Image 1 (cartoon, rainbow, N blue to C red):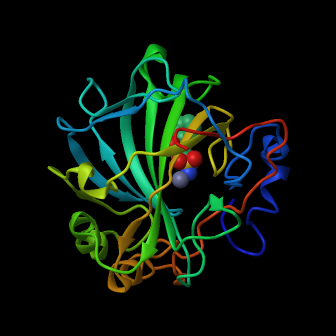
Image 2: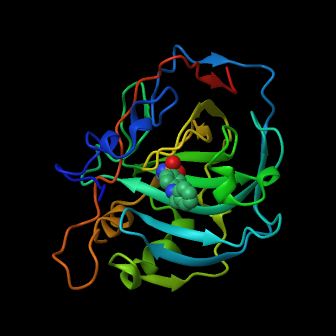
Length: 257
Ligand SMILES: NS(=O)(=O)c1ccc(NC(=O)Cc2ccccc2)cc1
Ligand SMILES: [Zn+2]
């Protein structure tokens, strides 16, 4: 099965998922000097006040904090988007070292980690239908650098002991994802894909310019998770990122000058 190792990692994915070599794959390098300001972009609207988190799951590739997406409770709108996109889960990608771990890069710079807040377009009724549409998903990407702690991340860090291995879940209610956002909502946007198999070309990417800072102790706790199941040989869940893919016939737009 696919993963992030030498024998099943990103260079192999195309054999089971030929769209890996498609026309709108993610992540990409964001060349800041080549992105163009688009004055018609609207400000983002992040409306997370009624968010209902339910559960945290180690799925063997990352950990997901899942939300109740059966009503408009935590939604993303505006920016490049038409319509209302409901938050279904967030997760991270991270490195074995502070010098790598993000999926997107900025002028070839890699961050220590990257947060993905995954949303789907309510016009398609459910997530499984949305991933089959070119405008089905909107993923809000936020870079993490190592420095000061992010207080709003700590509740996530402290539950990780309970979901160390693949297939473990834990109750995770009343978590407020607003505590994971930076001050500014300035962003870059482009059309792309899921960054893991099945690599579907269904995502409007919205990547914030301002990173959040997390502490060394916080990211070290991410690196204690396991890709394996309980009772299987231990392999640390680190370097669960896909490298930058060719931009091809796309322009990255910026919301700011
Ligand atoms: N790293 S990312 O945010 O691009 C990203 C976000 C989500 C997924 N996968 C699913 O959510 C699972 C699924 C896929 C297809 C159909 C039903 C379920 C992979 C990558
Ligand atoms: Zn992701």
